[PDB]
Image (cartoon, rainbow over all chains, first blue to last red):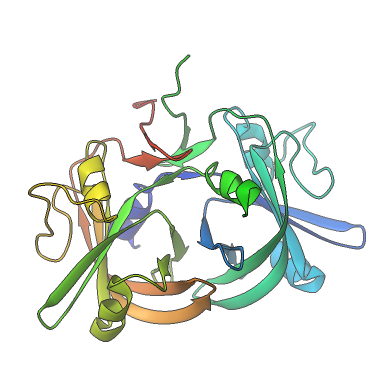
Amino acid sequence: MKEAFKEALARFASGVTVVAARLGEEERGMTATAFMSLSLEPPLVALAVSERAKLLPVLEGAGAFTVSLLREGQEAVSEHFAGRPKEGIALEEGRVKGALAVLRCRLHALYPGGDHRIVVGLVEEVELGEGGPPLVYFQRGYRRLVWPS
Amino acid sequence: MKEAFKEALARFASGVTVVAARLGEEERGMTATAFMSLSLEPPLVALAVSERAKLLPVLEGAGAFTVSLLREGQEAVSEHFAGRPKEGIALEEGRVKGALAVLRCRLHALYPGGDHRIVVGLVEEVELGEGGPPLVYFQRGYRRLVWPS
């Protein structure tokens, strides 16, 4: 169903992020390509989280979360937090170590989004990793950017 | 201000779209990288549109809009609808001709988003162009994907 729509979405390239939240010692991470900048003043970002995602209840309960932007070569991290377990992968400080960047947000709002919820975060803290190319998703697969030396 | 935050956002790669709407005799197009898939059932997409954008009131009044996903080689189209005019660039049938895909949406819902407005569209029609690599934006510049892979 929705073949044409899905194909259109498969034609929108995007970076790959890992959204994480923790309540006490209960921490959950979730891979997401549906992420976008929203505002500068105040600093806001938005993302789509499935209504059936185990992350949602934890994120809403915590009232805060982090967003890590994955770099080239981090396919294993993306797969792991997408529900396909990988060895040696674990969140550190509530985020992904070695990512291009990390945004620590407090929950700003939750709006209806069909089978997903629109999650808006107010960025309170930012962490930047080393520079370099990003992990990209396009046409149902991980891709690389032309970024020669 | 917000240097680290802006740098983090510059590290999220994305495709490039042109959002357009027509109200009466007024039609406007606007380049946007803040786009994301939102739901399958119903088929929804989300966009962040500047509260300063001339396109916003036209889109609100029309109750409908289009989203064109730009392909590699359409940098001039992106620049044009970003406010930097280019000779001969224009919308055709309310969208960008030769794009990778076009989504014709009914305005589903709107939400506050700081200095931007969250725009949710319900996809009613899909136009798919010929296959090929996309126009990508990353680190304050247009990039290309290593394609195929």
